[PDB]
Image 1 (cartoon, rainbow, N blue to C red):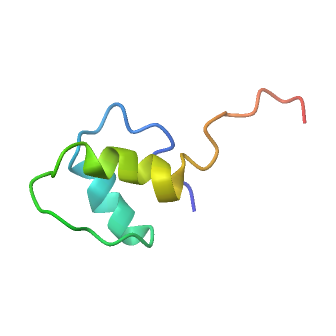
Image 2: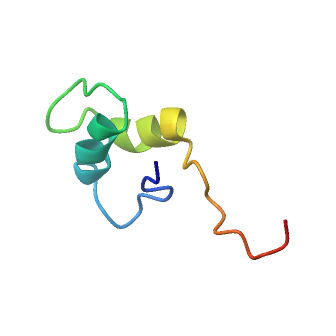
Image 3: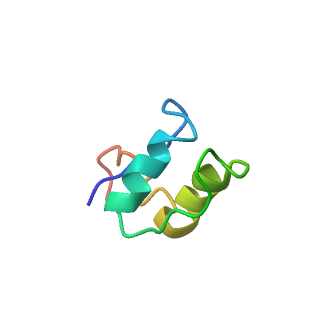
Length: 56
């Protein structure tokens, strides 16, 4: 399940439109305060942040 491991090009509303499909409830509507951004790195922790440079 790949997800925005680095949501710095979407916004505070896309990272959310995804979190939903990625097993994550959505609290406020507009955007509490970078809640969906931190939220993302919280449960999603940017799963594979590193693209793996081929070095095991």
